[PDB]
Image 1 (cartoon, rainbow over the protein chains, first blue to last red):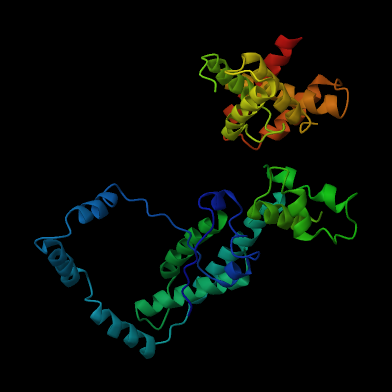
Image 2: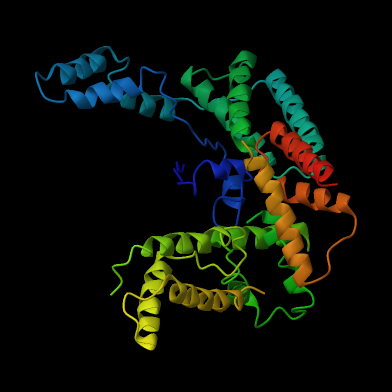
Length: 228
Length: 142
């Protein structure tokens, strides 16, 4: 089961940009992946000071390292134990969902489909697959396999819906239209397209004080999608 | 060799050159690069060589200057808000005079202006300000 950490491009503007469209030219990657979490490490004021203070010292008298070690003792499961536990639960029991939980999730997914369609009436640029539903399922069974129980419960899923909801919230988050033209080029410039190619828009947008790589592609991908 | 303190003048001349050529950037720029200030020097001394005169004149400096100027023109073809609108006025007219007479519906200028600045609008206050400013300028202009 693949766990992947991608690196996004250009920073915060990629959030200003459509949430997808990040990986290569294709969102399909993000479609295959169940749980996508673009993140923030907003240090609760005690974090940045945590790391800083840690850098300041980092010498004597191993007090901090010790503190880490008692954090390890107390730090819940010794994590050497956690492993053995995971093996245990993984081999022993295979969970199964309950019917009311099922119908619950039906309501879940149809509300998702409907509502977010309505959201996309405006052609709001972003998604929903039954694969995502199947994901939600696998989370429910996973967590059911935490409690080790042979059977699922409703509350048990009630967590999962909202967790994945946070994931959906993650799915949600030279002027473009001007460069988005290329249209003037596609027309009265080149019905063929040839001898035009990215190289042409390069000579057309090379000494016009104007075009970035992402800019050139964006407007291109845009018009490609737009249907112009 | 110019020791002469009329060289001070040259500065403003350099200075006179870039300002009017700052906006728009759609002019012949260039920048105008400091290397052009550096260029005016060798040009000056060149004209000195020409006229046998030593320490030259501010006038010869002006000749080299205008020379560079036509060489530029051949390449042509809180009030920041008012500046942006005045920039719109000069930009629209300068383009339309070269590719047209310019005239027509004054409302259109605001229309396409809002269409351009809509990309820079961070917040509704920026839109409302830009709209009321352009309107204020046109109302003042009339």
